[PDB]
Image (spheres, grey):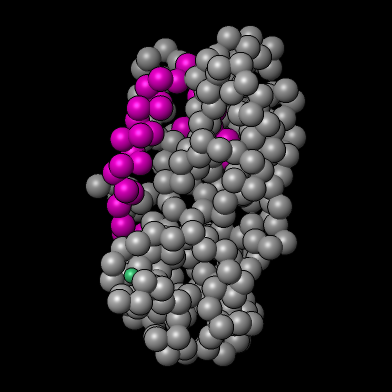
Amino acid sequence: DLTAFREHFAKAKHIAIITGAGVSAESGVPTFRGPGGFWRKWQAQDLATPEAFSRDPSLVWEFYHYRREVMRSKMPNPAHLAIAECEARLGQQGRSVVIITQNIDELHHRAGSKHVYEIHGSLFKTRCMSCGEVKANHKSPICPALDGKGAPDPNTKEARIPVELLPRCERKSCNGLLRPHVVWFGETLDSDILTAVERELEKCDLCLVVGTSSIVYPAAMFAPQVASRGVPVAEFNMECTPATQKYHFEGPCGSTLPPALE
Amino acid sequence: GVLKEYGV
Ligand SMILES: *C(=O)CC(C)(C)C(=O)O
Ligand SMILES: [Zn+2]
C-alpha cells in the first residue's frame, strides 16, 4: 500500500536509497550480463577482471571506451530525477537523503544527486596503476589512440593498441598506466566507503531499494542492519512477490518511484 | 575486504 509508505515517508528524517542495475537499465544502459548482453564475443564477467586487464589491456579499455561513449546518449530517467529532487527538497527542510549505488554510470550525478556513494566506482574516473591517484575524467576520447574504437559487433578487429598509448597518468614523473576506477570481479570494495555507508545506514529511518532486491548483493550486506533496527524497507523493482506476502512496488522505477516521492 | 558479489 502506497498510503502506508507515504505516511512513513512524511515522518522520515534520514532516508537511505540503495540503487541497483534496474535503474540504469531503464535509461537504456547495457550491463553486458545475461541473455544477449554481449560486447563482441564477451560478457562483462570475462572482461571486468584484473586478469583480463593484465592479459589484454587494449581490449579491456576498448570495452570501457565504448561504455563511456554510449553514455553520451543515455539520460537519467524519471527515477534518477525524482530521487535527486527529493534530496534537494528534503535537504531544505533539514532532512537527509543519501544514495548508495552499485552503478558506475554517474546517472545519479547527472540527475543532480549530491550525497551519493559509488561502491563499485565509476566509468568516468581513472586510477593510476603506478601511483594510485584517482582522477575524474570525462574526455571523449579518453585518449587519441582509442578515437573511434570499441565497436560492439562481434566481428570487429581488435585495436591491439600499444600499452604506452592507452591512457597514462599525467603527473609525468609517473606516467603510469591508467585503469577504470571500477571494482572488478574478484576485487574488494574500498573499505572507507563501507564504513561511511555503515554509519549512514545506522542513522537511517527509512530505506529504499530500487532496481534490485534486499535479498541479493549488494543490498543484502546491509538491509539486515536496518531491518533489525525496526526501520521500514521499501523495494521498487520489476521482481514479482509471491501471492502470499516490508513494502514492494512492482513495476518500472521510472513509473513507480516519482509518485511515491512527491 | 568484501569481494564484489561475494566472489560468486
Ligand atoms: C561490477 O558490477 C561490474 C562492473 C559494473 C564494475 C562492470 O560492468 O565493469
Ligand atoms: Zn600515476
Residue in the image at 45% along x and 77% along y:
A167
Percent from the top left, x then y, of residue A178? 39, 71
**A59 in the magenta segment:** no
Residue placed furthest toward the left = B1
Q: Quadrant of residue A140?
A: bottom right
Does residue A41 appear anywhere in the picture? no
Q: Is residue A205 visible?
A: yes
Residue A127 sits in quarter? bottom left
Q: Which span is picked out in magenta?
A: A185-214
Residues A246 and A73: in front is A73
Instruction: Find residue A186 and report its horizontal and vertical position in percent.
Output: 31, 59
Q: Which quadrant of the figure contains the N terminus of chain A? A: top right
Residue at left offset 65%, top offset 66%: A70
Residue at position x 66%, y 14% in the image: A6
Query: In the picture shown, does residue A224 fall above or below B3?
Result: above
Image quarter hosting the C terminus of chain A:
top right
The front one of A50 and A163 is A163
Q: Relative to residue A257, is residue A219 drawn left or right?
A: left
Name which residue lies at 53% across and 78% down.
A143
Q: Is residue A204 magenta?
A: yes
Tag count:
0
Give the x, y percent position of residue A82: 69, 33
Q: Is residue A14 above or below residue A150?
A: above
